[PDB]
Amino acid sequence: MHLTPEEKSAVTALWGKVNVDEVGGEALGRLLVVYPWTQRFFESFGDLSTPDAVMGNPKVKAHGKKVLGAFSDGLAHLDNLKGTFATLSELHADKLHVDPENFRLLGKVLVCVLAHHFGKEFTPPVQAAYQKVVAGVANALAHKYH
Amino acid sequence: MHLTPEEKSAVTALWGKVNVDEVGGEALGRLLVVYPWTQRFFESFGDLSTPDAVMGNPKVKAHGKKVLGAFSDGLAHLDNLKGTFATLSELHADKLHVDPENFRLLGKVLVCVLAHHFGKEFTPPVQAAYQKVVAGVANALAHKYH
Amino acid sequence: MLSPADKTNVKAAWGKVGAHAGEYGAEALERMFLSFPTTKTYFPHFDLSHGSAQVKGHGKKVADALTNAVAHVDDMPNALSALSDLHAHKLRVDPVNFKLLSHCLLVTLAAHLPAEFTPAVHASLDKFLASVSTVLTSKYRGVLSPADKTNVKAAWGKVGAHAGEYGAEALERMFLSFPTTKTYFPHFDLSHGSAQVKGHGKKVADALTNAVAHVDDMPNALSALSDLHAHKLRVDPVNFKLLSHCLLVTLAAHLPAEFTPAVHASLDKFLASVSTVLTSKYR
Ligand code: HEM
Ligand code: HEM
Ligand code: HEM
Ligand code: HEM
Image: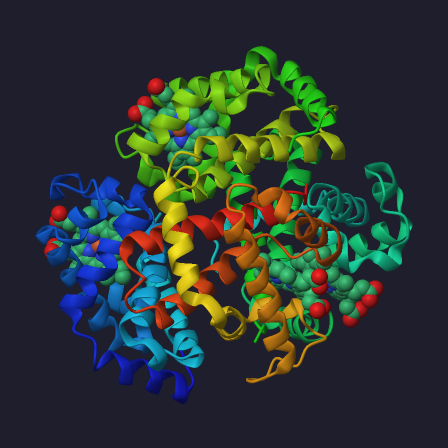
C-alpha cells in the first residue's frame, strides 16, 4: 500500500516506541470487553466474564502479543500487504473461520489504545496515517476468504 | 477488477436485455423512496413528496438514464473500472460533494431492481457476479475522494 | 419506527409469500453464501452444497421466525426475545452480517413477487428487516445499564470545560481520517485551526453534554436535532459511526486515567445510543 512520505514517517516513528507485548495485550483485551461477541473465538481462554478478568487473563495477554507481533512484521512491508499476510489470511479463513469484520474491530480498538497510551503525541495527522494502515492490514487479512 | 470469464459472460448476457432508460429511472426512483435522505441532492427536481411523485418525476427519470448510461458504458471496461471512472470520481468528490455511501446504496437498489425485472433468471450465481460489479463500480467512483 | 402503513405492506407481502416461506428462506441463504462468502464462516459445521437439508432446514427456521415477527409486528422485542438471547449469547454473529442477509431476503422477494414488490412495499420491507435485525442484536450489549450511565457521567464531568475543544479535535480527526465526511461541509474552511470547525465542535459537544444530562430521556432532548439531521442535513447514517470513533479517540488521548476498558465500553455504547436517536427519524 502507498502512503505519503509524511504518513510513513508518522507510522514508523511512533511504532518504535510501542512495546508490542504491552499494547498487544491491551488491544485484544479491550476488543473482548468492548465488543464481547468477539469472545466467540476464545472459549478455551478461560474467565472472560468481566473487564478485570479479561484484562488480567494471561492467555489473552499472550495472544495479543502474538497478534500484534505479526502486525508489527506487516509494518515492515507496507508496500505489499497482501503478499505479506496471505498465509495468515488462509489460516484465518479456512481453519479458524474468523469473520474478517473482526479485523476491522481490532483496528478500531488499536487506534484507541495508541491514543490512550501516547496522548497528545497521537495527533490527528498521525491517527489518519494509522487508520490507513489498519484498514490496509484488515483488507490484506480478508483477501483469501472465498 | 477481477471476474471469471463465466461471471463476465453472465453479467454481459443479462445486461443485453436491459432497457437502460427504464431501469435507470426505476433504480434512481427507488433509491429516493427507500433511502429518502438521498433526496438531498435533488431539491431542484421538483415534487418528491410521495413515492408515486418520485417515480413519475421526469427529472428523476432523466437523471437515472444518465447515471445508468454511464454504468452501462462502464461494463465494457470491467478490466479497468478505476481508469474508466476517474474523472467522474473527481467530479462527484470535488464539485458535487456526493458521499460515496450513496453509490453503495444505489448498487443495492439496482440489484433489487434487476431481480424484480428478471425474476428466476436472476439466479444466485448471477447475483453474485452483479454484486462484485456494483461493488467494483462503487470503489472506482470513490477512488478520488481525498 | 414502522408506521401502520409499513405494517400493512409487510403483512400483504408476507401473506403472498405464504407457504413458500421456507423455500424463499433457503434461497436467501444460498444467495448470501454466494454473494458474501465471509458469511460462511458462521456455518463451518454445515454442508453448504446447494439444496443441502441443513440449508433447507435453517431456511425454514429463518422464515418461521420472520412469520412470527410479521404476526407480532407491534410486539417485536417480546416476540423475538428468545432469538435475541441466542444470537447475543451463543451464536454471537457480528451485527454487520444481518444487513447482508436482509439484502438477500429482499432480492429473493423481488425475484418471486413481481406484482407486489412496488416501490412503497420495497421501502417497507427494508425497514422491517432492519427492525428485525435491530431486535436480534439488541442484547449484544443491551441498553445503557446504571454502571454505564455512571461511567459516562464521570468521564464527561472530567471533560468539563474542554468539551468544546474536544469536539473540534474530534471533527478534525474525522476529516483527516475519513475524507468522505468532508462532503457534508463544502461551505466550511476545514483547515487546521478553522473557527468554523471550532464553532461547530462546540455545538456538537454541547449537544452531547445535553444528552449526558438527559441520559434517560434522550429522544426528547435530542428531538430537534433528530428532525434536523433526518429532514434537512440528511447525513448518511454510516457517518455517525465515524464521528463516534473519533470522539472516542479524542477522549482517550485526553483522559489517561479515566479511559479504562470499562469506561471505553460504556462510552462506545453511549455514542451508539446517541447515533441511534439522531438517525431514528430518517425513515
Ligand atoms: C491484525 C489482525 C490479526 C493478526 C495479524 C493475527 C495474527 C494471528 C497469528 C500470528 C496467530 C497465531 C497462529 C499460530 O501460532 O499458529 C493467530 C491465531 C488466531 N487468531 Fe488471529 N490475528 C489477527 C486478528 C484476529 C482477530 C481480530 C481474531 C478474532 C477476534 C483472531 C482470532 C484468532 C484465533 C482464534 C487464533 C488462534 C488462537 C489459539 O491458537 O488458541 N485473530 N492470529
Ligand atoms: C454508479 C453510480 C453513479 C454513476 C455512474 C454516476 C454518473 C453520473 C454522471 C454521468 C453524471 C453527469 C456528469 C456530467 O454531465 O459531466 C452525474 C451527475 C450527478 N450525479 Fe452521479 N452517478 C452515480 C451515482 C450518483 C448518486 C448515488 C448520486 C446521488 C444520490 C449522484 C448524484 C449526482 C448529481 C447531483 C449529479 C448532477 C446532476 C446535474 O447536474 O444534472 N450520482 N452522475
Ligand atoms: C434475519 C435475521 C435472522 C433471523 C430471523 C435468524 C433466525 C435464526 C433461527 C430461527 C435460528 C435457529 C434457532 C434454534 O434452532 O433454536 C438461527 C440459528 C442460527 N443463526 Fe440466525 N437468524 C438471522 C440471521 C443470521 C445471520 C445473518 C447469521 C450469520 C451469517 C446467522 C447465523 C446463525 C447460525 C450460525 C445459527 C445456528 C445454526 C445451527 O447450528 O442450526 N443468523 N437463526
Ligand atoms: C454525534 C453526532 C452528532 C451530533 C450530536 C451533532 C449535532 C449537531 C449540532 C448541535 C448541529 C447544529 C444545529 C443548529 O445549527 O442548531 C449540527 C449541524 C450539522 N451537522 Fe450534526 N451532529 C452529529 C454528527 C454529525 C455527522 C456525523 C455529520 C456529517 C458527517 C454531521 C453534519 C452536520 C452538518 C453538515 C451540520 C450543519 C453545519 C452548518 O452548516 O453550520 N453531524 N449537528
